[PDB]
Image (tube, rainbow, N blue to C red; front, side, top):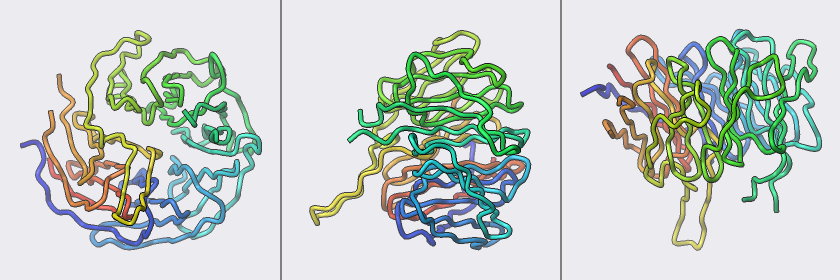
Amino acid sequence: QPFIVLGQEEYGEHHSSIMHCRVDCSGRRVASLDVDGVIKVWSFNPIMQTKASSISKSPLLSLEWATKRDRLLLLGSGVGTVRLYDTEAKKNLCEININDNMPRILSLACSPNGASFVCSAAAPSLTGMNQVPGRLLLWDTKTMKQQLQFSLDPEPIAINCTAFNHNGNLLVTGAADGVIRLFDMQQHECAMSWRAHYGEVYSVEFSYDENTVYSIGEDGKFIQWNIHKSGLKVSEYSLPSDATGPFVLSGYSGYKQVQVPRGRLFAFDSEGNYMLTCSATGGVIYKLGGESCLSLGGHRAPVVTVDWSTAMDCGTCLTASMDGKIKLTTLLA
């Protein structure tokens, strides 16, 4: 009963598997990035319409909408840079040099107050492969310099995912060593850290009331954690294996494509009561109360990343798959 499907449409401008697809802060624009460096910025009211296209030079690994100065997209590359992409002017404003030694920009989080961003900069993947050193850096957009290094204890490690709380006081992070680290933004040390997953942490998020954090990891678990009590599981659930991959699109050709999670694996409605996840044939929605309640379907290839935006009881669910197709499902509460 909780949701009714108003419609489902397909955005098909991408021709390679999707890496990231994120709705902007106004709920009206999508930025999506495929494994070939192609970025599309598009709208979906009341028709789908491409507002900008851009083919990236160098590999691109992360994508984050700026917070105060909307229409601005931050793109983290695989050559140790962050590119500021003006989706209105349809041009790159500048290319910020983060680090040559640790060129994989695996995560970007923009401060809700607009003056800084956090970025994960990781060593090249080892030739268990992501068990490599990483740094986590606070970058002052405004002097264009690195302001702060977060200490990663006990050792530097690649950070896969980051998320701010509403005020920007707290940053939750998930690492390739399975550890979750939670930072307050004046100090270099995490206020809190614990072993969360056996294998990599792929996505993290604060609950709506910011009393817990949610995580999803390589062990296939979705876990809710009390942030007043380090390592206190509030709850834990074993998801179907196609929620966490590795996602595989294969043919009789002897040919396969393999995607380890890189983009967001889970997304929530506005009030944090329901969770969208990946599966081989479309998005799957669960209820988070103290429970699969809707399957969105529509995909002929495995879904590898999702998003969910809410505007006033109208939700839109993005599901993105290895054939490059993005389905938009409109949900009414």
